[PDB]
Structures are given as C-alpha cells and as structure tokens.
Length: 68
Image (tube, rainbow, N blue to C red):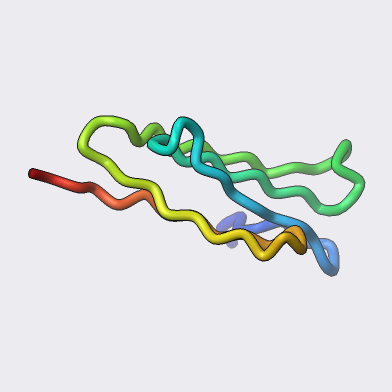
C-alpha cells in the first residue's frame, strides 16, 4: 500500500548530507526524468548525519538526533 523506494525493476537511490548537517535523499527509477522520489530531512540543530555511498547508485544516509 505505502509508497516506498522507486519500483520498476532495478532503480538507483542515493542520499547525501547537505552542509554536513541536513539529510537529502534522491531516488530515481532510471531515466532520471520521469518518476523520481525525493525526500528531505532538515537536520542542522543538535543533529548529526551519517551517509554511506557505494558509488554504484546505492547509498544510505540517516539523521540521528545528537544532544550535549
């Protein structure tokens, strides 16, 4: 039911950390100009971002709240 990831066989979805604080996720089916799922997590105040890129179109990033 819920829409997750980008269907249609194999797809490339990678995420990057903007400003080493904010998390941005980019998901594309393949054409990169038809159906894309983009998510944005506004992390910056007392929040840390961790990303892992396989350089193969597959990357996973997560935002974790960090406190003093």
